[PDB]
Image (cartoon, coloured by chain):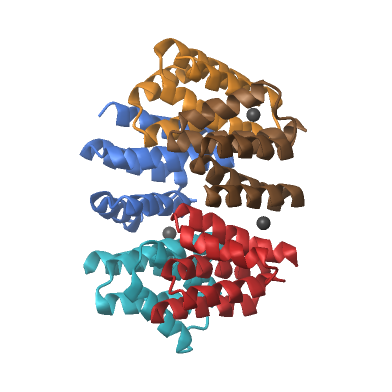
Chain colours: A cyan, B blue, C orange, D brown, E red
Amino acid sequence: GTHEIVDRVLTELLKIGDEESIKLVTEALEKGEIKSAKEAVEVIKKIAKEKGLKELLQVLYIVAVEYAQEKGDEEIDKLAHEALRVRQEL
Amino acid sequence: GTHEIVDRVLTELLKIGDEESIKLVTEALEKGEIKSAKEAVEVIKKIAKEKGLKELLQVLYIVAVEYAQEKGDEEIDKLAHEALRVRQEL
Amino acid sequence: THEIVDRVLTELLKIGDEESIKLVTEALEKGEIKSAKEAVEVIKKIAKEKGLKELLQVLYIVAVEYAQEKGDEEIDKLAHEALRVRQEL
Amino acid sequence: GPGGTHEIVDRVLTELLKIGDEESIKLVTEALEKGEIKSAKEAVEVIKKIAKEKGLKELLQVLYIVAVEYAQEKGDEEIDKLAHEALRVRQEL
Amino acid sequence: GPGGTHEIVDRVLTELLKIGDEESIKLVTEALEKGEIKSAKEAVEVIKKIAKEKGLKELLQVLYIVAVEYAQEKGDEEIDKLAHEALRVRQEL
Ligand SMILES: [Zn+2]
Ligand SMILES: [Zn+2]
Ligand SMILES: [Zn+2]
Ligand SMILES: [Zn+2]
Ligand SMILES: [Zn+2]
């Protein structure tokens, strides 16, 4: 759950070589800050808004919206769209 | 249903950085208008024909034929081919 | 029923082959393609006459993956003919 | 049998088209039409030797990828061995 | 056994071909051929170690992706933990 969102975000960040978001996301994971898939999205969303990381929010939208689709989870879908909104409003 | 079409369109728009189409599509989604995948294709195709958005229609054709293929939806398949006809007539 | 032509147009789009999209969509409009086999035959014939190597490339890939998916030996045979027609242009 | 034959050969041909390698395409399609390839294992073996003879590191790369993924799919340990062989041939060129 | 070893090693090689990392391909094939690997988990540890000692950032990126997806497939928390270690080792290189 936690790792399912986080690990995929990490993988997608490596593909675009966003090394700073990789560092920040992994820290949040290791700080014990993530206990659910839902928690992963809000934490990663918050981090990206604070540091102005448009590509992190793009990755986050894609990963969460597919996780929500795959699991039938309406809450994750909401956070994914809200991530893009943060991305727009940067 | 609705989000099945819209969310993949947004994901594909993100992959090519079509920031203009992303604005319009999430705007259409947020406006509570779209109640079905068929309405999703209709609204996006009409947006993109009005604005002359070749890349949106291409993404629309692909997302909608593959959705119509998966679920057996003759109406959506028709709408995808109409998306493509408008694009070629741009 | 026309699974093959849909996958062909998606691939033609990526390479921006608007002429093949046109000619392929025309064949679809007229009711010509009602099965996988007729999909490959009609598209291969159209690519042979109009001299479209890129269409035959796309058709081979699409047809051969379709054949593998469904275990359809006649489509496989058709896919390789389209490749041969390409190699002789 | 031809089931495994075309799974190897057709995916190799698909990948060669993607990189535009007409030289390999002609070499593989002619070996297939000449009856040189009657099983998955022979496909790998024939394409591997063709590529070694002509120094086609790009064809061995495709062959390795297609063969090891087929070997994992079918649990075929002989395809897997040939696949690693293809990679070694590529590496020694 | 050899199944899990090759599921890890073979995909790493596949991904290394895609980025053209011939230095890593050689070091990985060398470790495979030397019977130094009995399981998927050992494959990850040995590849992670080589990549640390030779400073191979790209091998570690490939290793994380291969190992973390294998771990998800197999419900294998030990291999997941290795995958994140591989990313940390890359961060310090
Ligand atoms: Zn993990
Ligand atoms: Zn959604
Ligand atoms: Zn259609
Ligand atoms: Zn074939
Ligand atoms: Zn192997």
Q: Quadrant of residue E2?
A: bottom right
D90 versus D20 height, above or below: below
C52 versus D54 height, above or below: above
Residue A67 visible from this viewpoint: yes
Residue at screen point 54% across, 71% down: A4
Closer to the camera, C55 or C80?
A: C80
Residue C6 visible from this viewpoint: no
Q: Quadrant of residue D30?
A: top right
| Horizontal and vertical percent position of residue C71 | 71, 33
| Horizontal and vertical percent position of residue A80 | 40, 66
| Horizontal and vertical percent position of residue C78 | 61, 20
In the picture, measured across the screen, residue B87 lies left or right of residue D21, that is left
A62 versus D12 height, above or below: below
Residue at screen point 75% across, 52% down: D77
Residue at screen point 45% across, 64% down: A63
| Horizontal and vertical percent position of residue A33 | 45, 87
Residue that extends furthest to the bottom in the rendered view of this protein:
A31
Q: Quadrant of the C terminus of chain E?
A: bottom left
